[PDB]
Length: 16
Image 1: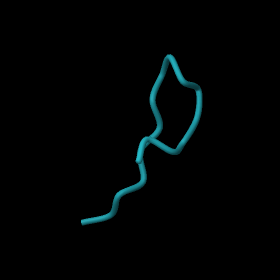
Image 2: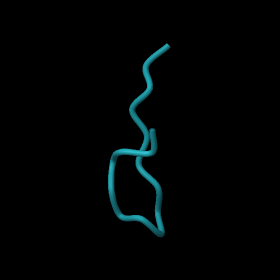
Image 3: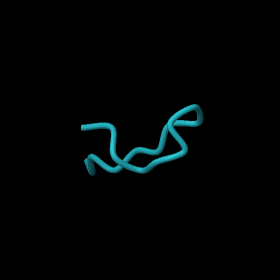
């Protein structure tokens, strides 16, 4: 159950 996400509008990989 990892917590690594990447939003599309944010273009990033940190949605903590």
